[PDB]
Length: 54
Length: 55
Image (cartoon, rainbow over all chains, first blue to last red; front, top):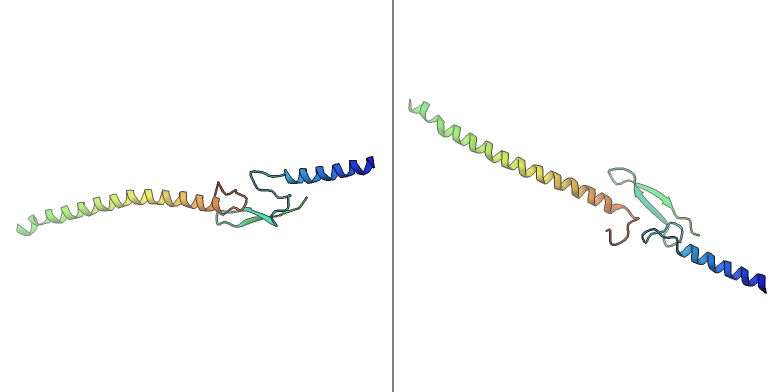
């Protein structure tokens, strides 16, 4: 029972650590978006970065 | 003599046209600077990573 309780506690801490991983309201790892695109040239070409849900 | 003396009006009109073109060039310098700033603003706005307030 003590081991399963510690296991559930760590499983909740994983949820909280994944939830807090934002930078100014945007996150590449919390799973709210499929990808982020950043500027790569003056004409507006994207620099795609696929999201990795955690 | 009347033909030679009539040229002063032509010179005056040419100077007035040069002055008008100069004022237009000053306004054009201002307009190109504003257009370049709008370029940088739209290019910054294209990025998907910004939050709503920056947009």
